[PDB]
Image 1: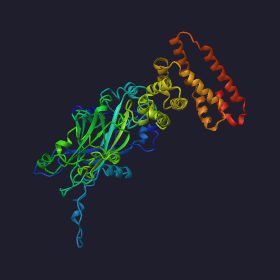
Image 2: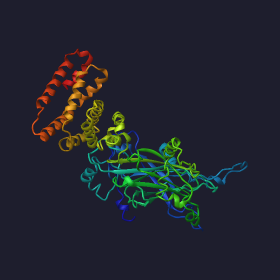
Image 3: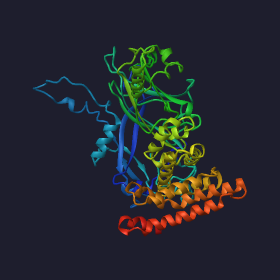
Image 4: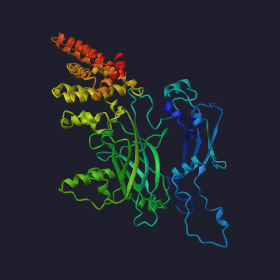
Amino acid sequence: EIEKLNNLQAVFTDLSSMDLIRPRVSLVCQIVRVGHMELKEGKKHTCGLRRPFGVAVMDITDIIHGKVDDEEKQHFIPFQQIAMETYIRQRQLIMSPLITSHVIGENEPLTSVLNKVIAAKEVNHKGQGLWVSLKLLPGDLTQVQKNFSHLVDRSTAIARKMGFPEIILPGDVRNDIYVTLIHGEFDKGKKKTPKNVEVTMSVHDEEGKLLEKAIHPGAGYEGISEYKSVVYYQVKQPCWYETVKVSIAIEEVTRCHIRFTFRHRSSQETRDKSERAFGVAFVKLMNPDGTTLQDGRHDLVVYKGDNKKMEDAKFYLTLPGTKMEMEEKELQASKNLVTFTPSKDSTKDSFQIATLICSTKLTQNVDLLGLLNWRSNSQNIKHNLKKLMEVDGGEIVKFLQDTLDALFNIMMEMSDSETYDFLVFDALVFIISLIGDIKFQHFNPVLETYIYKHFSATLAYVKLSKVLNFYVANADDSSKTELLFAALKALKYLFRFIIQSRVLYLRFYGQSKDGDEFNNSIRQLFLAFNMLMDRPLEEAVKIKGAALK
């Protein structure tokens, strides 16, 4: 692109304070040639196909540390090519030729070349490489584009960190579904040469319509309908590890899936286009329980058989897309012997992907939605409430407001059961404890936003006072000790919610017919703290300390 050579500026924002202080950081440029499979002249070869060339690595840890910051410096990153050493040394081997081997000069994945370049401090570039002026600019994208507009303008290419910052700004609307094609074992089958498998993954809706521009090869590049994986010249297990950008709208991603098509790519264009993708994978970005695809590894399964059937969104989507999916279907078919015949089409071919979902609304947990489905998951509310605290506060904070409202509504409808009251209480205590953390402090304003605006309780304060009074009356308990202690640590917003419920009661009933009862609750809480404290110090020294706190 002629309009990019003088505009090729790369910026990597979202580097948290933890990102810089990492011991070893390297800017790794992956160089992949696109075109002919074989550098041979005389016959037509399939063009437009991506082949591995080499990896260029420098330890920019000191550069990201800010140790050397100078615009005139052009740090030359040496380029290391894949070892295509099969022509120079082959000319001198006499008096004992006993060799039965092959040429491996392009089939190594870029992962191993990158590993070698990382290990080898000196890169035998031999005059091949690139120049990049590397600098660290403090602040976020706005500050870097405003404090360093000359350095970083709006046209400057922007790339984000593969992860999450130390500060989650409330409303960081992002759907960075980073799909990485780790590996896939594809059967050679009838073809003696291993198939030049390509992961032509494709984003289709539940109707199967391919969603164009959904897949982005990387930063600074527009999206594409389908992304092609790197060609490996007859590898049984082509290892790609290719990180791409998948930008699906969080509202439409609920009905969006990526269909991973793998085609055998013979050395000739006629055979290449005459060979259809022998096997296709796919994954729903949704768990069956109404939650989006989880963060981590997922092992896709390559199916075989009719090509029309395997492209039928009403058929292949119904088929288990992952190994865990086949295991789940088999186990559930083990308890029901009702029309469950496993198909021989389940070949041993499988595919592996990694999906780091950097999203703000996408939800990945079953217990969370079970509580969010409490009105119809009443049978598991006791289980869901216990199993909430295992869920990280990061997943909670996406819908903390609705979680609070659901807990309060659970209190509204079925307050008779005090055990669920205790479960909700302890879960909320954990909520406040985690939001008070530096990671989650920024959503405390959002928490207050819910309190002052979206809080929807009118008597929950009564029950909270009851339960907390039970805590303080049962202060000496060891099992309660941490609970009451964390309640102390969370008293502020606890009573903010209590008083909000009380004032909503007042404004929904005009005058408190139980204002005497409410203030009596306050006073009896006071005398309860008196009963807590008059006990000997030694049992609860830190508890009285936190009480004073």
